[PDB]
Image 1 (cartoon, rainbow over the protein chains, first blue to last red):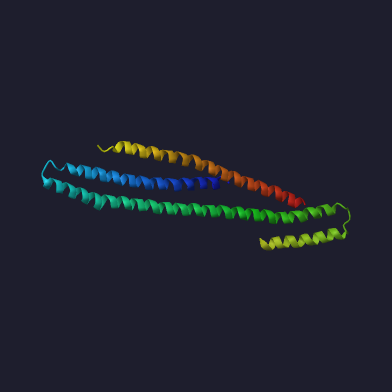
Image 2: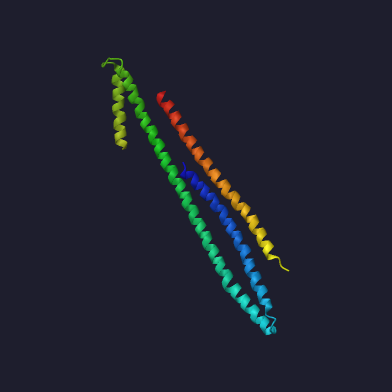
Length: 151
Length: 54
């Protein structure tokens, strides 16, 4: 019961922090573009040769190498998020199946314990030829044989 | 002429609020999940005991 609540607390934090990283990415791409195209405008200390040689380097390196590399890194983070969500979703199914198995076995053992207690009370009449106790013992024989056949 | 530092301070201050309340709410909802599962186990055990006595 404790791990099944830790698992929910991890899953909700995962889905919130992924959206905050996805917004951090877009706010950071614009900062890279601001810095690059603001620094490329300082190529007026030379002529327009110095201007085209700055904007060509800026728009080549930033739009051809840096922004696609950041997009590939974000796609990697997305695939990681999907894999970890499937891991948490499988752990929930494992815990639920184990708990269902245990409660089904508790009910199946209680069906034997009820007949054992009834036969133990029928012994207290101090009559071993009483038909009620004979029938309870014949019922317990079949119950125990069915339990051994199932296990 | 381009106030980028105040823009970044504003974005980070709006983004810290959300991190704080996600971290606060997730722990409490997981605790309530644990409590509800414990209550269902206690309910099962009590009604199974009374069933077996009846």
